[PDB]
Image: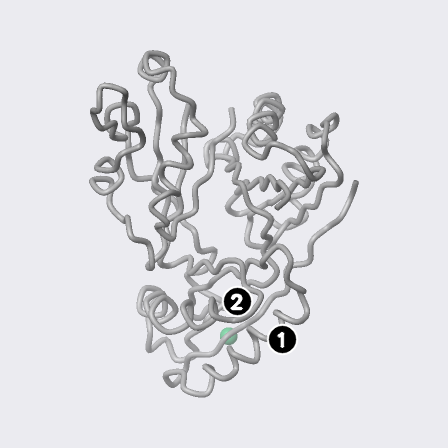
Amino acid sequence: APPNVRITANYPGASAQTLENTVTQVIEQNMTGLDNLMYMSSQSSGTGQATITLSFIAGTDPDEAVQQVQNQLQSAMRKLPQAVQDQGVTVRKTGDTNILTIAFVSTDGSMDKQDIADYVASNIQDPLSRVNGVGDIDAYGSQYSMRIWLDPAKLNSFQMTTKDVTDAIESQNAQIAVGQLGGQALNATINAQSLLQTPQQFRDITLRVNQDGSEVKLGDVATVELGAEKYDYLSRFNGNPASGLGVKLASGANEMATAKLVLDRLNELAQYFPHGLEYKIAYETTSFVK
Ligand SMILES: [Br-]
């Protein structure tokens, strides 16, 4: 059980070449001096999403490894493109990386962007998560951000730590992805599977039980607002209606074993696509530097 810090930035409209030089290369260079650090992997997808997963020595405090990095990111935010800052960089405790991005296209035009987006959610996402070796699967047309801002003054009063706040939301085992915006603010990713999908649900959870016995809920210390973001790069592929998904790989799993496993499973599903609906696959290679 090692620690792994994953960074996530997004610059919509940027080529893979654009993304790396302006973001990925810059962020890497701001991870200059770290302790317990081993090596750092990064990739720059044509999606417009940068990701620089970090890796530390065995016996490292993950939450403190994470807390440590955020402040080098504090210095890094300065240098990134305006819109990348506006988008928000997400720091998450995971060792998974994107390896495949699949676009589902309507050759006819008999299915609009949101029709296709739904079919992916219902039929495709779930059976591929069952594939041995899959860390996570993101149906972009079925996902969105929950921006959770935090009052300084409040957080000061409780003597609470943000680490607890993170785990408090992961404790319910809702199939959600919990990250942290560097620069306070937090950001969660919601799927179609998630147990909590609305801010009411987010506000109505208990982070901590006090010594006086009262319940502490998010809305008292955190302001929960929806984050308007476009998670899918695709409304059209080759001028044809399309929606896509990202395929993250589990930490220990072998890429190629799983890569075949999902695609062969995918081509098992591909036999019964509605007429017109095809798919286009792009492999997402990942750089390695130490
Ligand atoms: Br096409």
| Residue 100, quarter of picture | bottom right
Alpha carbons under labels 1 and 2: distance apart: 14 Å
Provide residue 284's location: percent of width, then percent of height.
64, 59
Q: Nearer the viewer, mark 1 or mark 2?
A: 1
For the residue pair 69 and 1, the one nearer the viewer reads as: 1
Q: What is the quadrant of residue 126 in the picture?
A: bottom left
The residue at the far right in this view is 290
Disc 1 target residue:
260
Residue 160 vs residue 72, the one in the foreground: 160
Residue tagged 2: 102
Residue 28, above or below 17: above
- Left or right of 97 in this view: 86: left
Q: Amino acid at mark 1?
A: Lys
First in residue order: circle 1 vs circle 2: 2
Callout 2 environment at 10 Å: few (<14), some (14 to 19), or many (20+)? some
Looking at the image, which residue is at 27% across and 49% down? 197
Up/down of 145 relative to 96, above or below: above
Q: Secondary structure at mark 2?
A: strand
Picture residue at 61% right of the left edge, 21% below the top: 75
